[PDB]
Length: 49
Length: 52
Image (tube, rainbow over all chains, first blue to last red; front, side, top):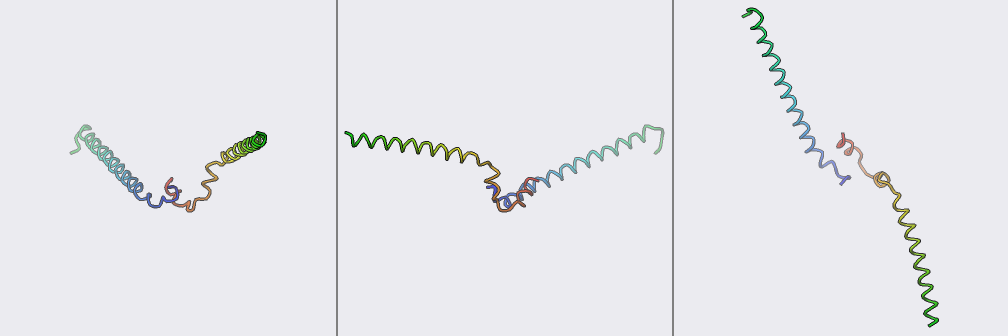
């Protein structure tokens, strides 16, 4: 079983990449909030509209 | 009787000699560690890729 591992490298690889994508999206989501909060501050500090 | 007497002793002596020899052989076999058996694997590249 240790001899033949070229045949089992793909599947794990897939999961790895998939996991990466998920992180990306989540990161993006946080970035999104960090803009809208900022815009709300705009409304609080005086008038800027 | 005496023919069987001086045959039983030979058989028993030989039996104990083999018992000693097989104890020795087993103890010699048990010292081979895993790395010795695993040094002969063909392609390390795929293995390293796997573990990384």
